[PDB]
Amino acid sequence: TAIFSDRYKGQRVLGKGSFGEVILCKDKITGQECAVKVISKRQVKQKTDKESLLREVQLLKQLDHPNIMKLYEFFEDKGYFYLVGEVYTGGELFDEIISRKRFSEVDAARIIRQVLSGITYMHKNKIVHRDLKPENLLLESKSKDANIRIIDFGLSTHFEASKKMKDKIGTAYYIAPEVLHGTYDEKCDVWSTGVILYILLSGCPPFNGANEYDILKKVEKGKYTFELPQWKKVSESAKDLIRKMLTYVPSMRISARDALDHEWIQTYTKEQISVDVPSLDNAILNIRQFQGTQKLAQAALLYMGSKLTSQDETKELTAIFHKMDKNGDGQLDRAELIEGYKELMRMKGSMLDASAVEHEVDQVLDAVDGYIEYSEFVTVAMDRKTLLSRERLERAFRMFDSDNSGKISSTELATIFGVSDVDSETWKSVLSEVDKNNDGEVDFDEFQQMLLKLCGN
């Protein structure tokens, strides 16, 4: 009865994840800005029947909490679902924390009370998150004390998530052990919050490891410690809340409601601070290292993924253009190049790619150009795509290189590649192939060369 394009217009992409793309859209009548989640039906398997999805959607539309992302509308066509909801521009919680000079137990508690309030409300309405992680914690502004909104509540129950490694990064740390074995309820959200809390107070995951399986092994046994030197500087009340949140048996684990009433929360979330605020210096250092490592492993997989996409394009675009060339003169006009690049985009699984074509064609013509030699257009068009892909990877590398040495050690490579599920011997062999005189260090171009060889390029 209702169609998406008649009510909204895509402005720009906000991101991509395990369910699909999140696009910044504006209402065509009211000018209202919002985040639209586009989910492909052919790409994403439905866990429940459409009737169960349509019912939860109606419930989510009726719910309102200051710590939960608002779902406004829901649309559906032949091959997609459209989850239209509120937009937040503050970015991810952890990306803000890493910019701070000081971080206290008060800071962490005020952060965790926000998360806990949202969870309590959702649980009251029988809605479980299940996949709660730092990436699901958005801010309204990139500042300290800013309001937190939890994204993706109830998504998990209806949609089977992406098993691709690019989407699996940073997930094993947070998952409750009962979710792994199949029997779980709302208590699984408390466990994930407890893991976030442990990281806020130490900058280290309680269940850590070299690769995904190793972390899952730790999670599954459920044993962790406060044995790190930075825990000496943390209050016993904070440790006692974590112990209750990371309690193995879900029946024996504290509720989201009772965690709000815990001594640490009620004491450290006072409007007027009544406690000592020493900075958790070692924690803030570890949170920057953890974050940087996560973001680099994410960027490495995106770069390899986007190279396995850019190789399809260079040959496919020259074919499309050759077909369009009636004269055989290797030339085309502005309209033909536009029609050609649009055809290349129509054969894929982004919604904003067709509208973005004209501006990109003109940007290529600015350096190139009438009657344009398509071969010159193609190389210039693909090189720009290659460059943007390289720059994204570079920003991540520069961010990870905290001491500005220009190099990453073999130890750091082991960690990055472990998080991105690249086999030790595989990456080590690619390293020997790239530089024969390698001495346990790679600069940005050697790193980029390594990832190229790791995706058959």
Image (cartoon, rainbow, N blue to C red):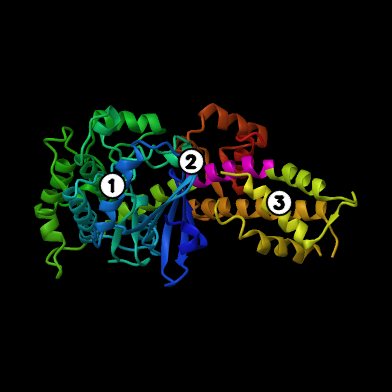
Helix, strand or loop at disc 3? Answer: helix
Dot 3 corresponds to which residue? 382
Can residue 402 be seen here? The reply is: no
Residue 251, given in percent of the width and then of the height, sits at 12, 35
Question: Marks 2/1: CA distance?
Answer: 31 Å
Sequence order check: which comes first, mark 2 or mark 1? 1
Which quarter of the image is occupied by the C terminus? top right
Q: Left or right of 258: which side holds 320?
A: right
Q: Amino acid at mark 2?
A: Lys
Looking at the image, the residue that sits furthest to the front is 1
- Foreground: 58 or 15? 58
Q: Amino acid at mark 3?
A: Met
Q: Within the image, what quadrant is residue 1 found in?
A: bottom left
- Which of pointers 1 and 3 indicates the residue nearer the eye? 1
Distance from Cα at disc 2 to Cα at disc 3: 23 Å
- The residue under the point 24% across, 49% down is 197
Q: Earlier in the sequence, mark 1 or mark 3?
A: 1
> What type is the residue that disc 1 sits on?
Arg
Q: Main secondary structure of the magenta part?
A: helix
According to the picture, the residue beneath numbered tag 1 turns out to be: 55
Give the residues drawn in magenta, as a range. Answer: 297-312
- Residue under label 2: 166
Could you tell me residue 398's position as x and y percent? 53, 54
Q: Circle 2: is it few (<14), some (14-19), or many (20+) Cα within 10 Å?
A: many
